[PDB]
Structures are given as structure tokens and as C-alpha cells.
Amino acid sequence: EASLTGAGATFPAPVYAKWADTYQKETGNKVNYQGIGSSGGVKQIIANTVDFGASDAPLSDEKLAQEGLFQFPTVIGGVVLAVNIPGLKSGELVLDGKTLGDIYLGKIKKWDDEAIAKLNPGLKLPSQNIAVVRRADGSGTSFVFTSYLAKVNEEWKNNVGTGSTVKWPIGLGGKGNDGIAAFVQRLPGAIGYVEYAYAKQNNLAYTKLISADGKPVSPTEENFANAAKGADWSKTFAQDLTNQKGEDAWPITSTTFILIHKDQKKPEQGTEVLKFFDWAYKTGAKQANDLDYASLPDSVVEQVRAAWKTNIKDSSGKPLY
């Protein structure tokens, strides 16, 4: 039995924790995962203080080669806008990318603003001020969210841009996906971006969004999967799944990655890390779906297995899988 430690992204933490609990029950192996944000996970794996790092933002091939790292995707999730608006039900409000960006820019300050009303004709919106909430820590969820906003709001693109950390025009900072969920829950009029599982598990209301194609869509596991239907995984695992075309394609979708060293100094540790993830691919789909994360296509996991064989080795050049 082995003890493994991983650290990073909170975006997939609910599913990694569930898989870890189940894996321990079935095999006795222990996986301790620390949700410290993608930026921290990258620093940790590079510092070699953990067996595997986790980040929703992919590293470029050149960055991977420079650090001697290998990266592979695990599941597909979606980012939603959790809101606390009195008298509004979950899924009733609809926002488009442009308007969402204007909210985060501080351009729109009340819930009954004309721009919001015209998108929601049947709604009686309250003249409640909008409390914008964003991440205080280096975050892969921030990366995905700002990648999306830069595509749909030129002013956002030109003035704040994309990144795991940006200079936010307005808003209070929350730590981790859990931190943002707690803020929305406690602040009447709040809007905050979180990975779907965090809104569902905390019973937070969320909005629908208008797809790249122009249709209002709901955030569901199937709709996250739909956004990924057109990704050419054979080209690269580092797929941008934001604002994708297609029916019922959730606009803020993203996969997430695990980072491990290619030259394993502690091969036993390396071998056990691959066994845990292989087990998750083979048996963990139901648990991922229970948490509303979509699974990667089988062709993609086969590509991952093939790459493990070629890339992961001990100091003697011996493959660990």
C-alpha cells in the first residue's frame, strides 16, 4: 500500500477526493490531495514537494520540456455564475458574454439594469446592487473564465486580459472555489464564478448562458461534454473549450490536468500515481458523473496510456507503466 500526495486545482477537487476515498476502500492505498489552486500546484510539482501537481491551465510544450514534466487531462467540468438574487430561482436568469464582461468591468451595477432586463423579458428583476466576487488566489478557474471573457468582451480583452491572476477592475476576493461559494451564499446580490459542483453542492442558484451559437443553454454534465465534441485531442491535450460552437455547448467549459515528472527519482511513487489514475479512468466514471463532470472519450485515455509508456521512466531509462 502506498501514500501519495497531490496538490493544486480546486476545480476538480470534489471528484479527486471521491476517487481517493473509494480507491482507499478498495485497495488500501492512500491519496492525500490538497486544493491550493492551480498556481500553487505548479509551484509544488516543480519544487518536488508532492508526487503530482494539478492545474486547469495547461503548460506549453516548451515549458513542459524545460521542467521535465508530463501533463495529462482527467475530466471535463464547467464554470458557472452562482448568484444570490432575492426572489430569483436557479436557472431563470440568462446572461450573454458581453453583458457578463460589463458586469465584471463594473459597467453594470444593478440587477435591473436595462442590459440585463432586455436579455430576461419575462423577469421582474430587483434593483439590487451587484456584488462582484472573484478569486484572490492564483487560479486555473480564473484562467478559464478570463479566457472566455477576452473572447466576448473587447474592453475586457484590451484592459484586463487573460491569466490565472489579473488586475480585477472590481470585486471582493475569495480563496479557492469553496471561498467564492461561501461569499455568494452570504452576500445578497452577489455574482461569483465557480466550477459547477460547488454551486450544486452548496445549493446556490446559477444562471444559463448564451452559447457561441446564440442559444440559451443550461449547465449540465452533457452540455459540458457537448462543448468538447469538436476537440481534436489527437493534436494536443491542451484544448481550449471556451465559447465553442454546437448545439447545447456550455460556453465556459474546461478539462483539467495532472503534472508529474518524466524522470522519476522515486519510481515506486511514480508507479503508484499512474495506477491510481489508470484505476480512475477504468472505474471512476460513475463517480465523476455523480459530481457532474464529463468523462474523457476512450480514445483520449488510450492516448494517455500510450504516452505514459513512452514518457515516464526511472533514472535508468526503465518505463514505469
Image (tube, grey):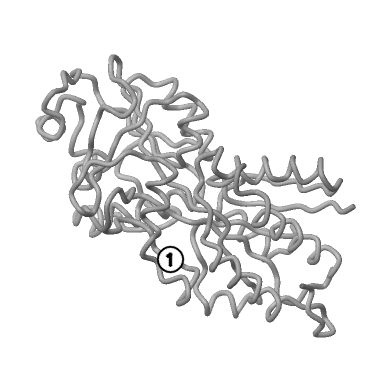
Q: Secondary structure at mark 1?
A: loop
Q: Which residue is found at the position 71% from the left and 77% from the top?
A: 309
User: Foreground residue, 244 or 168?
Assistant: 244
Horizontal side of residue 153 vs 136, given as left or right: left
- Residue appearing at x 48%, y 56% in the figure: 255
Task: Judge left or right: residue 169 versus residue 113.
Answer: right
Q: Position of residue 202 (x, y in %)?
A: 50, 26
The one nearer the camera, 201 or 182, is 201
Q: Residues within 10 Å of mark 1 (few under 14, many from 20)?
A: some
Instruction: Determine which quarter of the picture holds residue 19.
Output: top right
Estimate the x, y position of residue 296 in percent, counting from the top left: 52, 58
Task: Specify whether 46 is left or right of 188.
Answer: right
Residue 175 appears in the figure: yes
Is residue 49 something that shows in the picture?
A: no
Position in image of residue 164 (x %, y %): 45, 55
Q: Quadrant of residue 52?
A: bottom right
Q: Residue furthest bottom?
A: 317
Mark 1 lies on residue: 239
The C terminus appears in which quarter of the rendering? bottom right
Looking at this view, is 84 or 284 the one in front? 284
Q: Is residue 51 left or right of residue 107?
A: right
Count of labels shown? 1
Where residue 56 sits in the image (x, y, percent)?
Answer: 51, 56
What residue lies at 18% left-to-right and 21% top-to-bottom? 125
**At x 18% / y 39%, what residue is drawn?**
107
> In the displayed image of the protein, which residue is found farthest to the right?
1
Q: Amino acid at mark 1?
A: Gln
Q: Quadrant of residue 208?
A: top left
